[PDB]
Image (cartoon, rainbow, N blue to C red):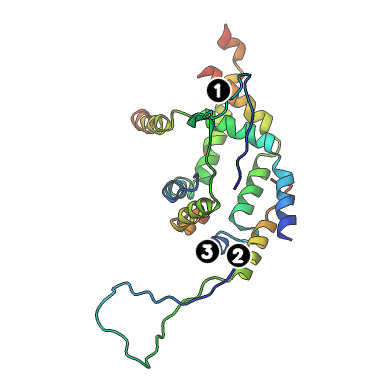
Amino acid sequence: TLFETITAISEQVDPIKLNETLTAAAQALDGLGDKFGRSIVDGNAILADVN
Amino acid sequence: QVTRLLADLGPTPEQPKGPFGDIIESFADGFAGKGEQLNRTLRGLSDAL
Amino acid sequence: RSLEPEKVNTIATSLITIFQGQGGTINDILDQTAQLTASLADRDQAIGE
Amino acid sequence: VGEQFIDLTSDSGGGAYFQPGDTITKATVPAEVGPALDAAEKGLAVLPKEKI
Amino acid sequence: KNIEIEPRGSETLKPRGVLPVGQTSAPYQIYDAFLDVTRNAAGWDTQAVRQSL
């Protein structure tokens, strides 16, 4: 039963689409994850000054 | 550790499908048909920015 | 290697902090930005000119 | 595969010692394989695969 | 355990030839995998993870 359930999930995983999705997500923020958070903080300050 | 993770993050009477089941169900229902719209929005945002 | 407890716990606590009770706020953001962007895009020819 | 045994674990590692004929009333037992298998099967089964 | 060879290139590997360290790899042990997954799962705050999901 456990093997059947894992096989049922694995048939639905479809690794090609997962591969392209994960590749796009990893290339989205490959070298700038601190930069995005710093930008969110900067935008928080900007909104606090503009509102 | 296997028993602990299966009990903590598994199905409960309150949450029959479990955390992962609920999140995959909500993400599949919450983005059903919005893939093309999201792709177009992301392309436009990237170009403009 | 991607299941390191420090990163998982930090991300989990941060998501709990950020998205707790913010459904109405995000709904308001989406509605207001949809209306504003639709009104702005209705003047596409004017903006181009 | 097996080879069960019993371990005596003391965090302090000092002080008073047990005397012959005494009894240790505090103990623990590892999680059984059967409940873990059942929990894994249920947790994997409740996931909607079509939604995946 | 066993060694798997994937032949590449045109030059013949002479007798007593030594493959470079950069062309060889060591296995990822099963006990290493169990150690990694168990040690990582030990430190998880499962309540926080479930609440975040």
Q: Amino acid under label 2?
A: Thr
User: Circle 2 sits in a helix, a strand or a loop, which is it?
Assistant: loop
Which residue is rendered at x = 37% and y = 93% of the image? Answer: D21
Residue topped by disc 1 = B45
Q: Nearer the viewer, mark 2 or mark 3?
A: 3
Is the residue at mark 1 from the same chain as the one at mark 3? yes
* Mark 1 vs mark 3: in front: 3
Using a 10 Å C-alpha cutoff, classify the residue at mark 1 as few (fewer than 14 neighbours), some (14 to 19) or many (20 or more): few
Please state which of residues A46 and B23 is positioned toward the viewer in this rendering.
B23
Which residue is most to the top? C49
User: What subunit carries mark 3?
Assistant: B
Q: Which of the marked residues, 2 or 3, is nearer the chain's N terminus?
A: 3
The label shown at residue B4 is 3
Give the spatial CA distance, label 2 vs label 3. Answer: 14 Å
The amino acid beneath tag 1 is: Leu
- Residue A51: % across, % down: 38, 31
